[PDB]
Amino acid sequence: RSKYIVIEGLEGAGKTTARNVVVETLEQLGIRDMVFTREPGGTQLAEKLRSLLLDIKSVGDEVITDKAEVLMFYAARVQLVETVIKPALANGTWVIGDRHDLSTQAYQGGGRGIDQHMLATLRDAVLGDFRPDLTLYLDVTPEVGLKRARARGELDRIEQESFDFFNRTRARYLELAAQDKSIHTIDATQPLEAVMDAIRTTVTHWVKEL
Image 1 (tube, rainbow, N blue to C red):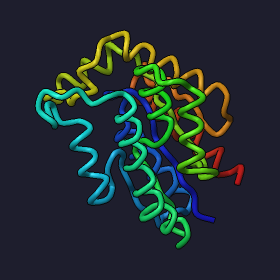
Image 2 (tube, rainbow, N blue to C red; image 1 turned 120 degrees about the horizontal axis):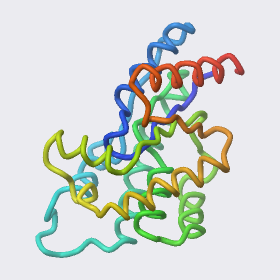
Image 3 (tube, rainbow, N blue to C red; image 1 turned 180 degrees about the vertical axis):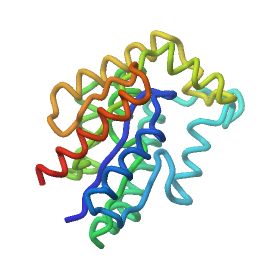
Image 4 (cartoon, one colour; image 1 turned 90 degrees about the vertical axis):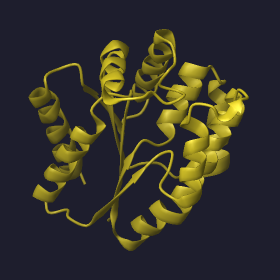
C-alpha cells in the first residue's frame, strides 16, 4: 500500500540530506516506486502562489496579511494534494513531500500567531481527513538554521523573519509533534552521521511496523 511521507523542519534543517536517507532506507526495504513533491509548489498554480508568497516585494510595497498568507499556502496545498499526491498514492506510487501542513501550523501558527484552532478548522475544511502516513520533523536551533540559510544565498520573504519568529515556530513544531505519534522528531542538532542514523532506524522501524 502506497504511503505519504513528509519531511519538516526549519530552513537549514537538512531536509534534502534527510530525504536522501529516506530513499536509501526505503529502496533497501524493497520500496522503489515513488514521487517527490515540495510545498509551496508542485503544480503550475502552486508555483505561482509560491512566488507570490516568498518573493521579496512580490507585490511591491504591499504587506501580505497573515491570513492571506495561510490561505495562499492552503490554495497551494490542496491543488498539489488533489492533482498530484492523491492520484499518485491512488496509483500505488509512494510520495515523499518536502513540507506539508505542519509547516502552516508551525510557521503561521507559531511564527505568525494565527489562532491554532482556526488553523485546524481550515485544515479540515480544506484537506479534511487526508494526512501524511509518516512525518519526520528535523529539529534544529534557529541560529543554526538561519546561518545555513544565510550561507545558501538570498533569503525569501519569510526566512527574513526575526529570531523569535523562528523560536516560536520551532516550539510549535515540537508542541504538535508531541501530540502525534505519526510525527517523529529527529534531533538535527547532532552530527550528520548521527542524524542520518536516527532517520534510517525511525523509518526502518515504521516500515517494519507496516
